[PDB]
Amino acid sequence: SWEVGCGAPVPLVKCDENSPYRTITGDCNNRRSPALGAANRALARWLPAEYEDGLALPFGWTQRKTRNGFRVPLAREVSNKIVGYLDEDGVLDQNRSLLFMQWGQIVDHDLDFAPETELGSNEHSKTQCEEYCIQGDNCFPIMFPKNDPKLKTQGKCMPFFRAGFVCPTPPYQSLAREQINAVTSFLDASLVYGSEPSLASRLQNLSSPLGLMAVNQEAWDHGLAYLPFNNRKPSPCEFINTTARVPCFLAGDFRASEQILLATAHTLLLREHNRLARELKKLNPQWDGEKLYQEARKILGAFVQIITFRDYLPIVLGSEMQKWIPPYQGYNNSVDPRISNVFTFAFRFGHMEVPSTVSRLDENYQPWGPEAELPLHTLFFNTWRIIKDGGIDPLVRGLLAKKSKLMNQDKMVTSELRNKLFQPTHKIHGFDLAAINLQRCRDHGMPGYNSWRGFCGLSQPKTLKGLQTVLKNKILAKKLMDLYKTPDNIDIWIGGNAEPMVERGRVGPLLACLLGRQFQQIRDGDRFWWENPGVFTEKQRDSLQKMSFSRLICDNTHITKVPLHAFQANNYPHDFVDCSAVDKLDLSPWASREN
Ligand code: HEM
Ligand SMILES: *[C@@H]1O[C@H](CO)[C@@H](O[C@@H]2O[C@H](CO)[C@@H](O[C@H]3O[C@H](CO)[C@@H](O)[C@H](O)[C@@H]3O)[C@H](O)[C@H]2NC(C)=O)[C@H](O)[C@H]1NC(C)=O
Ligand SMILES: *[C@@H]1O[C@H](CO)[C@@H](O[C@@H]2O[C@H](CO)[C@@H](O[C@H]3O[C@H](CO)[C@@H](O)[C@H](O)[C@@H]3O)[C@H](O)[C@H]2NC(C)=O)[C@H](O)[C@H]1NC(C)=O
Ligand SMILES: *[C@@H]1O[C@H](CO)[C@@H](O[C@@H]2O[C@H](CO)[C@@H](O)[C@H](O)[C@H]2NC(C)=O)[C@H](O)[C@H]1NC(C)=O
Ligand SMILES: *[C@@H]1O[C@H](CO)[C@@H](O[C@@H]2O[C@H](CO)[C@@H](O)[C@H](O)[C@H]2NC(C)=O)[C@H](O)[C@H]1NC(C)=O
Ligand SMILES: [Ca+2]
Image (tube, rainbow, N blue to C red; front, side):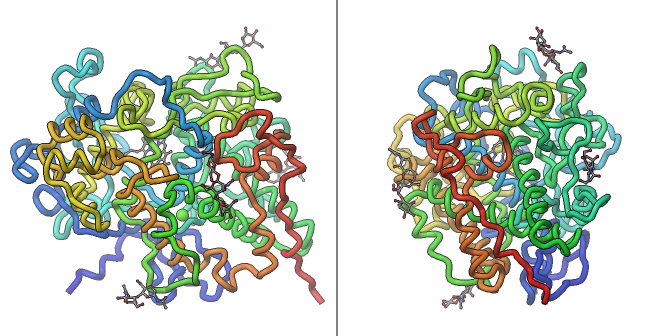
């Protein structure tokens, strides 16, 4: 017995079989088991879920049931006590560009999404939850602690709605609650093309057979493209400045306009597609609307994979890279490519990497104008700033010249995300990403810190002093222990991120294991991995290794000076070489001789 069946509410179709192109939904990747890795199926479970009532109610819900004989602390008090700080000076990561943070978020959005539950295209629950903090059904309010300033000016709580879950929607039972992943598990650039057939089509330029992706028709950027605007009303990017009224952008992933430096990357990517498609059409003039589309689309997914495995992972895992992700050896059809529920929390380490301001630089990399640097919190759902204040360039240069925040145990998440986050549904810039992350662990039913330590074959501290040694911090260890009473109860997000960093890495032992594990699996489990023999020819592969994030900027914006290594901290102008000195992608191996 297994319950095996539940293959209900999800998009299904026919396996094109032998087709050299991925499906949009990720179906048909694994032949013997066609729905592994597909958008709209449950997050995988590496360990059984731990819910309050065994089946679905999160810990903290019933105000009188303990977890291990103890009351779990309030998300927001774990925030106020451990995650907060006030001094931004000293905080910058001395050897990582602001693009280090930015790439983690693009990869993240390619791999996982647990959407909120709706049940109201009008309903008093999307307002009985915000107005009265009444816990009930999918309303699971983040209550304020006594002494939280936010009591004085905001209300009794921050509203929060539980995540969606497989099988039906309505009030549900039987099995443990399993959250949905609305995105494909494969590094396949789903964030650019969509994970659904319908959204995928809307995105395309289908008025002409050049296989181009739709581009905004209302605004231009020095004759270079922007993403289309969204039909969607109401529109939070609009609500952010009623005078400007500039809507959010339409991309293959819905979160694209969360912040300005993420809308920027989306737009460098769309631009890469269209570029690829024109170039390809020149070489092979008989190719197709569809054929141009898929071929450019296959080059792009190779891109996201190569920069990810070659440039970004080696510097997150550090010395632990070799031990979790060994060198590639071929597609293994038994490896399970599905993104695990815990990964979507482990991958939240990047939160502690976001700094507090965003800069715009002019052509010599000098402060563009008088209001160059801005508080991150005015940039949530802000598109009016790209469109009406210089477009993309001034904002890509800041990504190469400025630095990510460094995780630090006494400074974890800047207040910009911690006190001032705009959620695209509600009205204020007053949410807290840290508390939300914690409340979210609980909703998704996560095993505690020791469970995962156990999982990764690392010691499990049971006492103050043990916790002190693992964390190599006396004080942090003391706060955690005062809020939680036992390490067994420490939520994985805050435990994972509290560990000191492995050598040359930017996460700890627990985090290197869960990430390292996930990445090995999605590479080993992907029939379309770029080095998978028979997916690109040997000469195409040789061409694809020369790609770099720098080139991408050269070919797609008017920046003429860039770093060679783009994730490392780089000083202008010593570290900046001219575009000409940067290897170009040689598209000639994609030539198709008819006779
Ligand atoms: C604003 C937000 C960011 C930048 C200023 C930001 C950044 C990151 C980075 C750098 C990540 C990894 C390197 C990363 C991972 C994931 N985040 Fe994201 N994030 C901002 C805002 C949010 C919000 C709001 C959420 C949702 C919180 C919730 O639980 O409802 C959020 C989530 C995630 C996430 C989980 C995705 C999923 O599977 O649902 C990451 C892996 N971020 N962020
Ligand atoms: C800032 O971080 C840089 C990130 O890698 C680092 O430079 C890199 O140092 C590592 C070893 O710590 C080396 O790893 C490389 O080894 C050779 C390149 O010579 C390659 O064959 C490997 O695949 C791998 O890339 C490199 O020597 C170097 N890598 C790069 C990309 O240049 C700097 O040392 C850091 N700066 C400081 C002072 O901390
Ligand atoms: C709402 O969005 C508006 C932009 O679409 C923005 O107003 C704009 O911003 C500044 C003023 O702060 C102006 O920039 C400069 O414009 C002219 C040059 O042509 C100068 O002479 C001015 O002195 C000024 O420095 C924009 O022109 C201005 N535009 C309009 C129509 O008001 C608002 O700032 C946004 N408000 C919020 C709350 O974010
Ligand atoms: C779809 O593609 C066509 C072909 O590129 C676009 O039409 C061109 O767009 C630009 C900007 O308006 C102009 O040079 C011409 O108006 C068009 N040129 C040709 C060859 O006709 C069209 O804008 C694209 N549509 C969308 C929605 O992005
Ligand atoms: C592909 O990976 C699978 C999945 O882990 C491997 O299957 C294992 O086979 C080994 C022998 O090498 C056994 O020790 C394990 O108990 C098996 N585990 C599972 C989960 O099946 C397998 O090693 C790999 N196959 C190839 C040819 O690389
Ligand atoms: Ca994907």
